[PDB]
Amino acid sequence: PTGEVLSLVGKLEGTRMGDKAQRTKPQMQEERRAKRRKRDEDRHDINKMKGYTLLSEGIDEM
Amino acid sequence: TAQCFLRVDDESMQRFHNRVRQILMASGSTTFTKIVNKWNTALIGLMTYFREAVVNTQELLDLLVKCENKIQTRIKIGLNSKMPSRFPPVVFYTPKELGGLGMLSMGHVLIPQSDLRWSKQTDVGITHFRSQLIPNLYRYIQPWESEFIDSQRVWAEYALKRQEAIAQNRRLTLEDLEDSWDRGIPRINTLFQKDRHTLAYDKGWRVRTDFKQYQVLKQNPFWWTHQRHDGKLWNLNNYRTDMIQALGGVEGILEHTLFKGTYFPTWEGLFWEKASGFEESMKWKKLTNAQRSGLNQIPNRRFTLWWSPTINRANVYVGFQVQLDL
Amino acid sequence: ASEMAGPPQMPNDFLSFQDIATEAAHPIRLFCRYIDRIHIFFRFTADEARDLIQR
Amino acid sequence: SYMLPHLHNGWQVDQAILSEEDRVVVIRFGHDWDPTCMKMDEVLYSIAEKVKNFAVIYLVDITEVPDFNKMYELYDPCTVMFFFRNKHIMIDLGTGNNNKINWAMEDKQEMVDIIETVYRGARKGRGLVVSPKDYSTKYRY
Amino acid sequence: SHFDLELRAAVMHDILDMMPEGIKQNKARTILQHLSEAWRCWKANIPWKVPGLPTPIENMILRYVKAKADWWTNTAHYNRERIRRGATVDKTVCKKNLGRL
Amino acid sequence: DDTNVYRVTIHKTFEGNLTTKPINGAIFIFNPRTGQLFLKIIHTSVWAGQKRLGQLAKWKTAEEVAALIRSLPVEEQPKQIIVTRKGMLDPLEVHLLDFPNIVIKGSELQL
Amino acid sequence: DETYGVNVQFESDEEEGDEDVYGEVREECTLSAN
Amino acid sequence: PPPLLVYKWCQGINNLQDVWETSEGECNVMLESRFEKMYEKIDLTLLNRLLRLIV
Amino acid sequence: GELDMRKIGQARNTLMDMRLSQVSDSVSGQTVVDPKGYLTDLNSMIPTHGGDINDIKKARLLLKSVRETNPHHPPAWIASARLEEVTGKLQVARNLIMKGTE
């Protein structure tokens, strides 16, 4: 059994090209999820008061 | 209604062969790792451009195996001036970070059943264990037709989802479109880049990259795509992991190395110190060309010492034993 | 060239004609220039082929 | 032409070898009309003024001065030998023998490295030095 | 292969032969440098004209340069044909051929 | 304690512009056992126009404390140095290499 | 409040993988011959 | 990408109108050419005049 | 005599250029700006102050550290906003100042 590598001609019968391929997953998926969750929580105040044009809004003073 | 049969142009075949010839000739006094990196880059370029045509072409496979064998023979000649027999494939095909050359394979290499046994000694005593073919690139690369159909489908999906999101006033999150992460000729990944707004003004980028050949001396194997716009069109982490497993698991690989000699309790917290040598690697200095060549050989010295146990045996080299003095 | 490019208001995509009659109106059915390489696709009927060969 | 100085007898050869004290003496043994010696002499002429600082070159015709053939084993077309302060220096070229060159190389840059390494080893005191390259293979690809 | 070496050596011998003894002890290296300069100028495609150089020696140098240029072009083309068709070569030969081309 | 090394004063002129004046800081080196405190003054001129990032300031404070340790005799030299700021120990690890006998650590507690 | 007295830290922070910090898709005369 | 260009070319050729029908005696022709010396033979004065229209 | 080989080429070039300009005269919609007017506009537009960019970035990092260290330094927030509005754009200053106000 020499170490020579052998031509693949005639040795592809049992296999396809897309077989064994794999597609990755978003790196730090959960860390980014947590960062976005914290950002949403801390920015909830900014979002809530964003569209409230106070002069034209009568509930802001409350 | 019709069938289209594809092949790789003889001109492209000749260009790849000449690229390998240039790598070999200019190899000269260069390093094994650089030679293997050049080979990996060339093979990745060819195999990612001509995906199905390579399989369809019965001459390109033979050319690929011939060039791979030439590269391996170059490494062996550099190792020693006398050709061995049944050289082990672990040194070539082991990942770089684990001490190997991290070579990429495109042939049918059979790992002998002998190499996969490995021993381990503890207070109890010695226990012996065992674990096949090297994975090939063509399996892990995806066909162009599937790429295109899936791209059409996934981008239609994204159009629908984006319409729904504009209806809801929100932006699309990473959580949605998650199943479609790596899909689409313009990859869905590129849709989240910071510089998307800036890139929106880049036009003629494909032809510009194609023309770069008249401005930059280096040959670009990826002259047809840009990581910024088209995204990454392949993925080989699976291939690396399967290469480790086929070589026989981390312990099986380390058996051939000198790692057990270091007597490190475990292989977890260890780290290589690239380009240090005994002189701090003296990377910056006004040394002569011969001195610089010696430094460039130093990494080959480290590699040869690291893989010495599996390279320094009578099975590999016919018996002409000479005991080391003292 | 105008038939292939379509009217200025709604240009056609790479290989397509606003109407199949417009597509069939000419022997040249497809055209594509790379940086400097040209690929053309003609379709002749018997009479046009014979006349062109005669010329 | 061969404007490089030529040595005509063993007396001249030994006097030239002993004359230098801080420069490596290079001797090309061979016949000036042999094409291998022609190529070697061309390269040596090119590198003369480059390595004048620490080396001096000389040429010997084997027929003119055959006394050294037996002791130094001069039977190949062209050979190159290096001396320093009456000591014969050896070089580990990897060709199999570390005494002489015995063939013609074509790269003046590599010849310069050989001269520099031999001089440095001689000054450091080593009787044998290691060339910064292996010639066991002709590195043709 | 070494046709250029042979041609240069023959040219040197011929020019030195009739050259009077009294001044050849001094002008040999000068004429060699002149040959080198003429070859360099031809290679660079620039005029080469030494005002004080006698016309017969000028003609001799011109003939030498013409012959060497013929051999240069022919060997460059042949070596390129070899490399293109496919024949093992090395870095220095490849670089020299690239420069000539 | 190297927090107080770089401090600035923001003084307002209500019309025309605003000015920030970098003022002198202090590197504090305290001895819990004997209570001896070496406070190294950091003049404004050191960093008023240095044209450098923190890649100068961190290694500057590290080299200043290393110089103080060098000047101090070995008998009085410490073998344990605890940094209040966690982003300080690494440049110390680099700079006090000449004195491996010391142990550089961070302080989970801030004084 | 005047709050005179300020401390400033310089760090080489803000290292990221170049992706969006939050995983969100942030979207936002003629010629004539006479 | 060029592979997708090739795929689109093939699809368009196949999707032309009754392209593969050759009962009456039709004929399809694919021409491929290179535009020899495109860069080298570019008259600069004419190129300048042409550019002045667009730019 | 001799031939001034250049001349005939120059004559042919001039003939072609004159003919092409003759044709171009019919074309109307072309655009061409006045170089002196544009150069005058640029020379006028050259800024007289602004702010050295390296010093601006140093001040930006300094003020960022200031504000982050002190959540309650209205002078710091005002200084950061003033810098961000004198140089750069104003949306970032507006967001930073909403943050500082809160």
Image (cartoon, grey):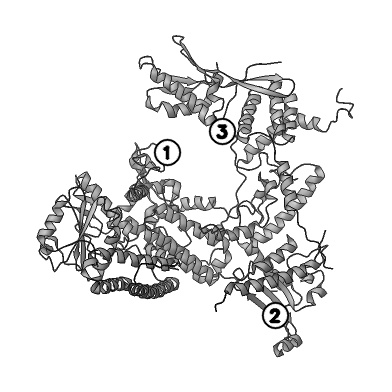
Residue B323's disc number: none
The quadrant in which residue I19 appears is bottom right
Q: Nearer the viewer, mark 3 or mark 1?
A: 3
- Rounded to the nearest whole Å, what is the CA distance between mark 1 and mark 2? 67 Å
Report helix, strand or loop for mark 2.
strand
Q: Quadrant of residue F109?
A: top right
Q: Give me the disc on residue B270.
A: 1
For disc 1, the chain is: B
Horizontal and vertical percent position of residue I31: 77, 58
Does the residue at mark 3 contact the one at mark 1 (Cβ under 8 Å)? no
Above or below: residue D108 compared with residue B60: above
Number of other residues with Cα within 10 Å of mark 1, as a class: few under 14, some 14 to 19, many 20 or more:
few
Indicate the amino acid at tag 3: Ser
- Whether callout 3 and callout 1 share a subunit is answered no
In the rendered image, residue B221, in percent from the top left (x then y), is placed at 54, 59
In the rendered structure, are the residues bearing label 1 and label 2 in contact, judged by CB atoms less than 8 Å apart? Answer: no
Q: Quadrant of residue B283?
A: top left
Circle 2 sits on which residue? H28
| Residue sitting farthest toward the bottom | C54
Q: Answer with left or right where residue D53 lies relative to residue F48.
A: left
Residue I101 point in image, percent of width and height: 75, 24
Gap in angstroms between the C-alphas marked 3 and 1: 27 Å
Q: Is residue I41 above or below residue E20?
A: above
The vertical placement of B203 against B8, above or below, is above
**Do marks 1 and 2 share a chain?**
no
The circle on residue G12 is 3
Label 2 chain ID: H
Tell me which amino acid carries mark 1. Leu
Confirm whether residue I58 shows in the render. yes
